[PDB]
Image (cartoon, rainbow, N blue to C red):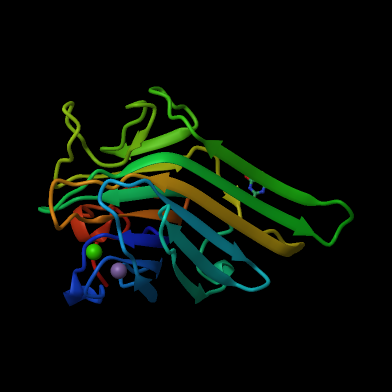
Length: 237
Ligand SMILES: O=c1[nH]cc(F)c(=O)[nH]1
Ligand SMILES: [Ca+2]
Ligand SMILES: [Mn+2]
């Protein structure tokens, strides 16, 4: 049923399902088997930052992930998102753990979307920026194990009081309002997403990752989408 486009920060290589032999970024059209990837030098415990972009002229989805003091990693993939995704969509952040685990912690998240038409002065827009997550955050649809307000943060995966991550966990956060990505009289459509995070683990091998995703508006966590499926897909096809 559900329909997914996402940019994965895969902290654990499941090389039997096409993950490279290390931590990587990647771009998932309707399949966790990333159509493109590139190497990611994840840093256990540092605050990393993620920049997603597309426009309907270039029909290319490109992302850049960047720790301070450090080189960025970038990946891109040419796709017409209008030939993939429904005309109305919800955007979100997903992450997960299996028998390996990490903190999956959003410190900030900031979407922008524009439709500009043939007409004079006719942009249509939605921005949001969260630098501080509330306990009762009514503009976010929290799903599965995702919680807010903990040091004013979004906790995609489960954490215990003391402050360390639980395995076999999946959670997502979706912005309450739909996003129009296409309109008949569109001449350029665009979107960018930024978000910062703190993946952290007591282990040399953390799993599984964080995705920023764009989905149908009724999208929900598919069964057994813990671990390698990142809360996005029900299987690995
Ligand atoms: O891309 C968008 N344009 C206008 C809107 F109101 C919205 O939610 N999304
Ligand atoms: Ca993986
Ligand atoms: Mn991958």
